[PDB]
Length: 240
Length: 240
Ligand SMILES: CO[C@H]1O[C@H](CO)[C@@H](O)[C@H](O)[C@@H]1O[C@H]1O[C@H](CO)[C@@H](O)[C@H](O)[C@@H]1O
Ligand SMILES: CO[C@H]1O[C@H](CO)[C@@H](O)[C@H](O)[C@@H]1O[C@H]1O[C@H](CO)[C@@H](O)[C@H](O)[C@@H]1O
Ligand SMILES: [Ca+2]
Ligand SMILES: [Ca+2]
Ligand SMILES: [Mn+2]
Ligand SMILES: [Mn+2]
Image (cartoon, rainbow over all chains, first blue to last red; front, side):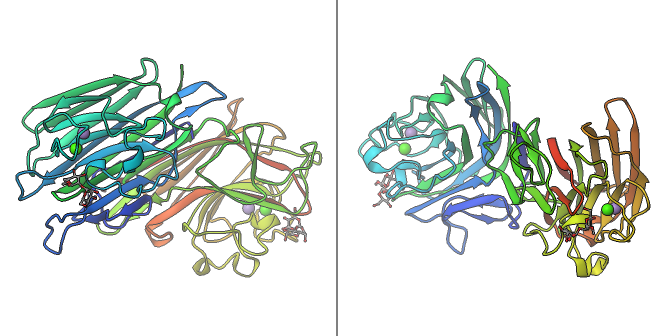
């Protein structure tokens, strides 16, 4: 289909079109990307992702068309620790994408350690909300919580300072305009605090024509819950 | 998802979210539901159906919601004969639905011979465009070409006289309003010739909460191509 869209105002446990990977599972009408104990408390060493089952037609070689897509979603992180980790990410990858071996912790369940920074070894575009930046383990991160745009590497091609607010929902709008090739990210907290980051990227050179969209999150030694509360997505092929 | 929509202005051969059953396949950016030979002519004894991969949330028992859906599509029928058979049908059925054994010909690939008219043995709502009505083989049909609304039976609960035009595309709009429970069908040829048929049906008592939508076509001894040219679909769960 040239156009596809779906909306999850909430996530009832009765799901049919979501591909759950790792520890990801539905709880309290929300997606708990990372594992939590019987008390709903976050635990260490956990990775989880969800993908919408239907493949998205990102671009079409034959018609020279590229998709105009928008992904609106909200999530919240919670942790009794002063340094909750590791972060959540909205990502776009090949349809057969699975959790890479050893992709936990700072790699957000998106990259394998050996090629995490090899842009030629990956095919993924992701908007990460990174809360752990310990300069000894996450050597690639700026020294502070941030929102980053990842293109075939865990080393964001771009980051903007971000504030982590325990238990507060962040509303995020990620849009891609094929005309300008601008990938825009706008995130806001309920008090009006706003964060914006944009990047020009030709998705045609990074991802295959058909892809799957979803979220990923992980916790290494430090942990926190990564709760996806809602998600709406829409894409439509346009001439360029 | 509470809401889902997809649109196929045409049907390129590189499909990822379509379940093809029987003889259905893509040809010339269109879906040929029934089998055709090398030179593109319709053949006898052929059944074919397609279903969108993503399951549709037709209704939700917990929230007492029923989806409002709209299915817009166009098709054309071509046949060297002028007794082309048997017709095409838009249908909604449980997710695991498959072509019933012996559902060819007048059964449109939707029902099994032994239960074709047993309403309690089926789970399917279809909008058929029936071109073959020989009373000896299709004993359940009115004696003329017709558009029918099928609810768990090949014997339409409601029909309207229809005109088969060889090679001409029929534009169809199928809508279900959960508020009034009316399933409305509007079909028009490019020249404005219009056909309407509607029926009140509580989809909750007929279909499970999650379903799959698609098309089915078949030709018995009489044949014709059943060419699905375009299809857009959208459903949104609503409170009433
Ligand atoms: C101390 O470093 C680990 O934890 C931090 C914070 O969670 C991560 O950012 C970092 O990637 C490290 O996690 C790795 O090591 C963990 C312990 O072996 C393991 O559980 C993780 O999956 C990851 O490999
Ligand atoms: C006896 O009529 C056959 O053809 C008409 C017109 O195509 C159908 O409406 C009717 O169902 C009959 O088709 C059946 O028999 C065919 C030959 O045995 C078979 O190919 C069909 O699948 C169907 O069973
Ligand atoms: Ca990090
Ligand atoms: Ca018939
Ligand atoms: Mn980072
Ligand atoms: Mn009929």
